[PDB]
Amino acid sequence: KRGAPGGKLKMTLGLPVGAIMNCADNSGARNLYIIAVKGAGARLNRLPAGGVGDMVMATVKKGKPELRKKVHPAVIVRQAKPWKRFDGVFLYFEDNAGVIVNPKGEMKGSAITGPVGKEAAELWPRIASNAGVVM
Amino acid sequence: MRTYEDTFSGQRIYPGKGKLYVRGDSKIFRFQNGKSESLFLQRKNPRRIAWTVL
Amino acid sequence: SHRKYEAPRHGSLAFLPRKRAARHRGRVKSFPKDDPKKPVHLTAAMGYKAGMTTIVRDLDRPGAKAHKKEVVEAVTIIDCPPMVVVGLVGYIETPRGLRSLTTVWAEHLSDEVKRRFYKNWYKSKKKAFTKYAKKYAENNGASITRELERIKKYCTVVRVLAHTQIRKTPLKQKKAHLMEIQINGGSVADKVEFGRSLFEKPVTIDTIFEKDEMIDVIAVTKGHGFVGVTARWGTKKLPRKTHKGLRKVACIGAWHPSHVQWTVARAGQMGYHHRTSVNHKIYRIGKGDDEANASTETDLTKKKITPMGGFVRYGEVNNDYVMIKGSVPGVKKRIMTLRKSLFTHTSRKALEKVELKWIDTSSEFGHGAFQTAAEKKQFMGTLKKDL
RNA sequence: GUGAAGCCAGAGGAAACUCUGGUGGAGGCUCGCAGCGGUUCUGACGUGCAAAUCGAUCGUCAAAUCUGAGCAUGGGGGCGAA
RNA sequence: AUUAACGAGAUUCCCACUGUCCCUAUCUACUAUCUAGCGAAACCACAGCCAAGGGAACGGGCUUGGCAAAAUCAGCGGGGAA
RNA sequence: CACAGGGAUAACUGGCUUGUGGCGGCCAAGCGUUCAUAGCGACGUCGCUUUUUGAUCCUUCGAUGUCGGCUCUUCCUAUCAUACCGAAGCAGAAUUCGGUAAGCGUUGGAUUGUUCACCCACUAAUAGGGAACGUGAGCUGGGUUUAGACCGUCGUGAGACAGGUUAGUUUUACCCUACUGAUGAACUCGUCGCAAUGGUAAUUCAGCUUAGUACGAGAGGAACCGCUGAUUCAGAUAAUUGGUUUUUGCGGUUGUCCGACCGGGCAGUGCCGCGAAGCUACCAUCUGCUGGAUAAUGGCUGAACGCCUCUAAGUCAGAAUCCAU
């Protein structure tokens, strides 16, 4: 089946195609270059975009040479644009980060550095079992 | 429902107002308006601002 | 040749004639279908719009993500001073439509309604219904009771004439508003008997509507002077290096259609149109005499719904009011019209029973921080002006 | 702004000659005002202020640089870093 | 065939930067707009609503139909094969 | 480079024809485990279209602005996806052929001036065409197609090349009509109402459950209701969050001027921090209804034809269709 989370409530989409975010695990990569979004629709002239919690197709631009020149799935874990939940509070992190995952959902790495958003933790069980502080 | 206090100035915060900030070192800051956070991100000392509770 | 890449059209042709509304007051076009087994009841109301505020409540929607948790929603406040009944009308069925054949008025009319029939009231003689009033107390009002008997005989629907008491609001205007409200009830004899008994009496909004009911709002939207295509319809802007303007439409038609067609976006007037927004919900009906109408079951503070410093560009609400979820068309001070719904609701979301938990009463003139004046005094301390 | 020949003082070496600090002020060298020119926006205007102008941005600026008045070359002829 | 320095010469890539773009929003000055005074030019067979037909093979005027109500203001760029 | 002329004569549209290009039929030798027609079809033969290219030279040479892209509206069906159905060498899943149907959609990027093409990725799907080969007083000027210059082949030479390369001015609307909005004479001035005709709007997917169930030796592996969300579109609104600053509102500071302090001028808004009000954003919030008549198809009673048959008379159900609310 195609990879797109179900039950995701609407939130502001902070990062479009072409954004470069940081990497937050010990896989060996240092940055991620975004090229597609899994749940994207069709509309003339409109760039696809994604937010915290949805899966993204990305390539690495700086890291171990074994990992370069390929295309990997990835999941965003924190974004730098404010957004609000149903509780009415606006919040935002300091930077953009993501992790490399299997298409099924398993993480390639073993540990996560820094905080993670609450929505990303709930949707993907594997990331929740590995992260530390949430929100 | 509960109320919080601004970290920088100590003003009362009611639901739906202000913002919430999470730093790289996993520290949590709360603000009540735009004046507080603009001074906080400017690296100002709250002990030298005359109208703060502290 | 064909269009290269496909795209949907801009705007909608349903609301096509984009001209200023013919009348300032909103107009109701249809009424709920009549049922002769219900008790007689009115089906409309009318009031003035004060402003908006924020509430907090917990959600009851099984299977949802936010189930049994607090949510924050926006609401709207409508001022609703009582109305006065003035008369009633009857209609008959004809092969060309409906038409009215009779109408009767009450003996005494207030100076509020009489202002409506004049354009220069100050220098007039105010002789509006002087000769009509003598029809009472003349042959024991024999002429009046004949017309009432006619409606019981030839009519099928009956409406009532009512007006507002604008003198009980902070508005500068003194001219009242008049409209017709249809009576849906058991029988034609019951309709006229109920309507006639209400002459020169006040009716409150709590008798018409009740809590958590799904209603419709009809009004006239906010106006803008004269706008271009980019903002009126929402078309893409032209490149930066365009000569002779870049906020236009590049091509407005082909050659042998040979005329500019009615389906092409063009500049003109925007706003001040008549609109009908449906499916709004009522959270609370507050009484004006109560001095703690803005309190809830968990928040026991004794306060009224008026914010600190009063609503911006409006006075304060001292009469009854209704709280409506969401937004409604119309600017502040404008007259609104309320109508019972035409649909049937079995969605399990419109059947929810709402109970509030907190109501915001902070100042909307700035970054307000306190609810009441007593609470502010305790936190702030004592000041120099307090002597 | 950079600092060419010439000159002064000290040090090393058997010798031939070599190092270090100052002095000096060369070049169809360089940044950059006035003057002279006219690359881009394919900007303004395009029955214009104007039968070639206006604004911002640009090239050169002590030398094959800019310029006034007097005199010479006259149509199959003149003059031309073309 | 190579080539240091130089170039308002042609081309490809990287860092910094940004409303070029996703996707648009707001503010200021002078016009456009209304008034008093002054006051031109291009152009013009007669003129000015459409569908089909036939015709010099793409009609505002002909034939058959649709239709059709004084006098007017601000914009617009489909047509008058302007 | 010039003059007198030519639509008696070419390069672009339009017109007739359709060889070539595209699309659709008829006959049945054979292929298809065996069996012409589930799905195909040799040798032959009958047609349609004007988005390919030719043939012709009727209309324009006292001029109809000649490639491509951007923007925006509408129409055609030879149907890519969606609704409901008929067939199979259709167990399930996945596929192939056909009917009613144009209501609603059909994308983001690397290289090329490209039309055309080719790869990466998303998606229910990335179908094909017309409107003077739609669209320059709408834009752009990369290509072609004036004058400068370079190379290769050809010419004794001036010079030639549908061979390559670099730089090259894009004018006017105030008139008529058309379109979008705004006033308005006559029957006294007003308030409250009816509705002829014209317009019309929504769209698709995913998760949970049904269920590791039906089906099958196994491998594999569905659907109706119900619940909750999301994509594209439309109409409003500003309680909260973000943007805008001539509120020149308060504060900080450089140069100069009023003898110093206080308070001020000038530097077309000197500059910086915060900034109410107003406007505003799928960068923010709210909302988007159900009756009638049918097409394809599957049926009932029932003759013509003593049997049979959905049709001949009559009649039932029925689609994102049509007409109304």
Image (cartoon, coloured by chain):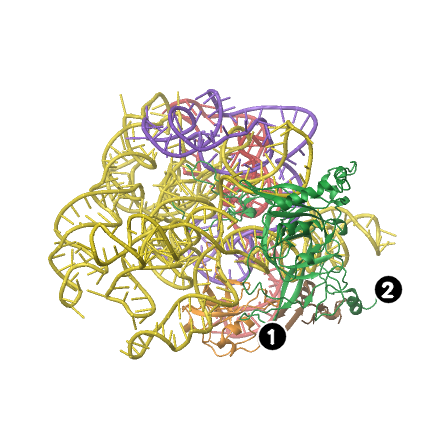
Chain colours: A orange, B brown, C green, D red, E purple, F yellow
Rounded to the nearest whole Å, what is the CA distance between mark 2 and mark 1? 45 Å
Chain of the residue that carries numbered disc 2 in the rendered image:
C
How many residues crowd around disc 1 within 10 Å: few (fewer than 14), some, or many (20 or more)? Answer: some
Observer able to see residue C110 = yes
Q: Give the x, y percent position of residue A46.
A: 48, 56
Side of F153 where C162 appears, left or right = right
Q: Amino acid at mark 1?
A: Ser
Side of C241 where F132 appears, left or right = left
Q: Give the x, y percent position of residue C178.
A: 69, 46
- Residue of label 1: B26
Nearest the viewer among F120 and E64 is E64
Report helix, strand or loop for mark 1. Answer: loop
Identify the image quadrant of residue A68.
Answer: bottom left
Nearest the viewer among A109 and D69 is A109
Q: Amino acid at mark 2?
A: Asp
Identify the image quadrant of residue F45.
Answer: top left
Q: Give the x, y percent position of residue F172.
A: 52, 33
Residue F230 higher or lower than F280, as above or below: below
Report helix, strand or loop for mark 2. Answer: helix
Residue F42 higher or lower than E67, as above or below: below
Observer able to see residue A103 = no
Q: Give the x, y percent position of residue C376.
A: 78, 66
The C terminus of chain C sits in image quarter: bottom right
Side of F325 where F242 appears, left or right = right
Between marks 2 and 1 in the image, the one whose residue lies nearer the viewer: 2
Label ID, residue C386: 2
How many dots with numbers?
A: 2
